[PDB]
Length: 48
Length: 107
Length: 49
Image 1: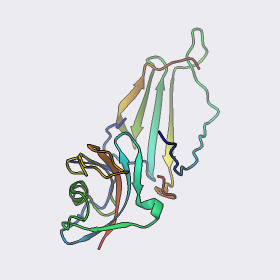
Image 2: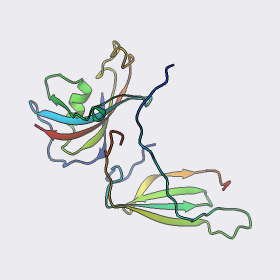
Image 3: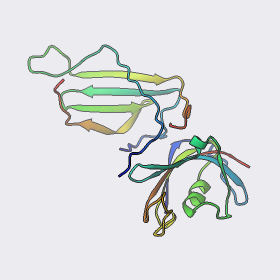
Image 4: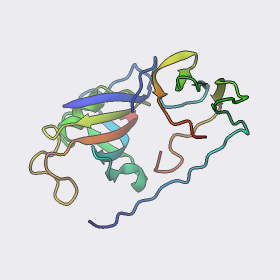
């Protein structure tokens, strides 16, 4: 599912991906090179 | 028509001009996700001169917007593409085409 | 109808030994953060991306 980030590009050298997990919501979020990634995973199962 | 989405950036300065040969690698997929063509499997880049009409309209216009070193995804409607007649055996009628095109150089 | 053949690259997954979850009465903190830095990528080592 395409997601919008500044300077979109397929992962390339010198790229830093920041992954954030909030089990409470539950939500998973991403940042690209310190820039927000405009998409989230939520409402996912917590079985494990 | 042609919808272009940049997978990887190019130089951003060089764009194909009419009468200029474009050398590309491409992988061809239908909108359902099935692959019907790839120049990389043959290991030989595909060369086509802009404005001759060797390739379909979708390729002409989409590569026109591309740049050297640029990798892009091109979505081409049947009207641009082979259309109702289709490409027998390969492409069904009224098939939208998705292409992963890397513009290696211009010559 | 017919079976289809194509060449595909192998893929492998690597994880750290960190396991975090949510449960009632759990001892585990909910919010977690990590990063991955890309040193080298070869876009087309094979025909497949």
